[PDB]
Length: 46
Ligand SMILES: [Zn+2]
Image (cartoon, rainbow, N blue to C red):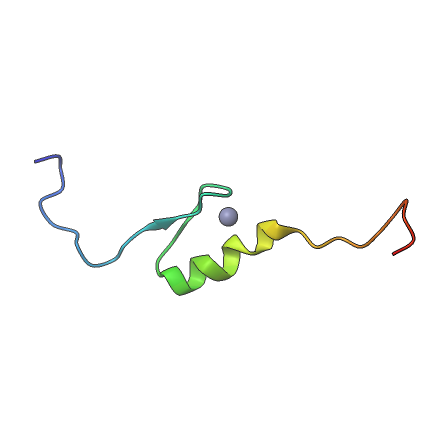
């Protein structure tokens, strides 16, 4: 037992991108997309 007697309930989904945590996955998945970074074209004419 590794100081984990009780807990099974609120899976602390950690962001593999930054490394943060969220109470619910529905709040993390929507964040894991923030790293995508969709910046416009600069030096190129897009
Ligand atoms: Zn993140």
